[PDB]
Image 1 (cartoon, protein in one colour):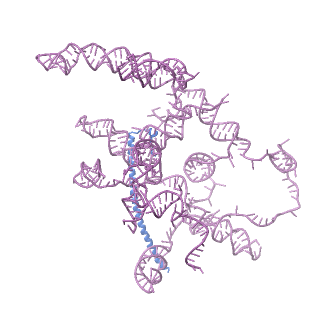
Image 2: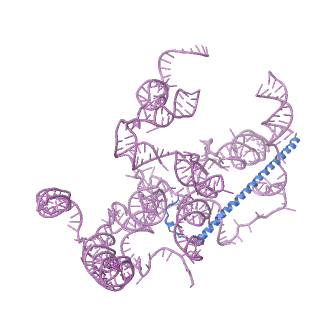
Image 3: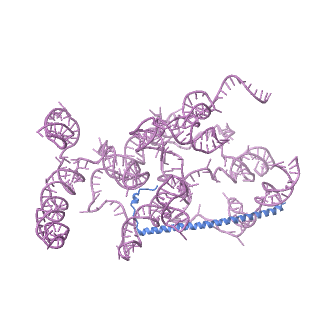
Length: 83
RNA sequence: CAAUCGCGAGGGGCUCCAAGCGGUCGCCGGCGAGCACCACCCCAGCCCCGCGCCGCCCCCAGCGCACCGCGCGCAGGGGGGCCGGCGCGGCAUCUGGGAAGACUCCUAAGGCGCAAGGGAAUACCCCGUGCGCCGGGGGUUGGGCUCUGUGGGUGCUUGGCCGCUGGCCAGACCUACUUCAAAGCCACCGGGGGUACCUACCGGUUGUCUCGGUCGGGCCUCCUCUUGGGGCGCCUAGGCGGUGUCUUCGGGUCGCGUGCAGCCUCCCGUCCUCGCCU
RNA sequence: GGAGUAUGGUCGCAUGACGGAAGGGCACCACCAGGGGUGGAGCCUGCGCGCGCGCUACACUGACAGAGCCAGCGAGUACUCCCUUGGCCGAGAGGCCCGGGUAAACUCUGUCGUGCUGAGGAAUCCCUAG
RNA sequence: AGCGACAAUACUUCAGAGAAUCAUUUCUAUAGUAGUUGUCCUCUCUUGUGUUUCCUAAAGGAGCCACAGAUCCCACCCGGGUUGAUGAACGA
């Protein structure tokens, strides 16, 4: 729950001035630009990953057609030459 | 309360009425409290007294208005009546407030504080967890929690020990004596499966050499694990804490300009939302 | 080459039946006790002017006015009833501002006093503890 | 409709090579390869295992009476204390 009563440890603290205030503000603004930065970079690595697995799926379809044509022509060959 | 007595607003011609209000004698009336209406101090107020300002009224004291007049609009000198208010200073008392004595008052048998938790009339307030502080009650030359030890008890009471019909609790003696091995049965390994070697059992074979067989076992194999399960993590919608901008308004501020208009760096709060923390 | 499994064309074929008695059991399509409808008026969906069914209206249980006091289901960046006389900002299209059309109940306490301000024929139908 | 063919057209399915190591309480068939020893002294990291304990975090007490001991706490008193007790992050 949110606390509506300012406790003593909140009524006790040190109000901090301009130098450390601006060190806090600069440090926050850097951290937000880092978070949006890595959100972009991993969005684009995810997209390129999806293209990679897509075309790997198509090339394994063609590998399956090599399997079926090769085994079918085989059992033509020995399938005829056993009789 | 009971007997009694007085005055007299207010109204009407020394008299009349009355709202009211008091006194005296009895109270085999009842209630309440007794230093203290005091001590110490502070803040005011009533009154009386001091000294100086104003507020007002004075008298002399000059221009314009009527050169057929007073007085008037006003500039203000110096003193006066020193009249009252106000200001300041005491003021033996009286009045009120606060403080106040530790017998007193100290809100009650309970209260207070700090820190957390929950709810709001969201400035205030309210309710009952952890730490403390006092109090009431009770209270025999100390008390209390906790832990540990020993003895008895938690089933009806007949001795300690031995080579026990006897002996010993200080022990003693130590090694004999012998005619005749044995009756059988039974005897817990998880399931399926393999069988070369060992073993078991069955049937043998020659002369103690081998062979064949069998719901046993040794040995081997694959199940007797991988769960309608639990724990600990990861991930994450989100919440909270710390915290930072953005909008909006109100203040505050360094400074510039013309110190108008404004510009203008910085600070605080509100509104508003978004954000970030190994 | 085999095996299937499909797909689409081509061809041939023509021991019974019916009752009666008496005895059991059950029923708001029965008796019994009651309660509720619908059917009088109006609006109406439906079904075939008619039959209904839902809803509205009609008083003692009134009307007015205060005070008090109670629910449970309900959460998709979702939800607004109209259509406008005007005016703003509008070169133009729109957005604006101003006018027109968490309960009922219940409790308790006080003011008026039946005052077109009248509860529905025959019938047939339903209903037995939250 | 229903069977039979009677051919076509699709789909699906019907092999597995090479090399090495492992294993027979020596030797998996290979001589093309560590590894025939009861070493001495320390330190560090690390897998398990027993017991005891605490937490996650509760639960249940083989229970009674007597006597005794101990740590701790409170009370009293003593000692040092506003000529400074206690708390409390150091520049010479």
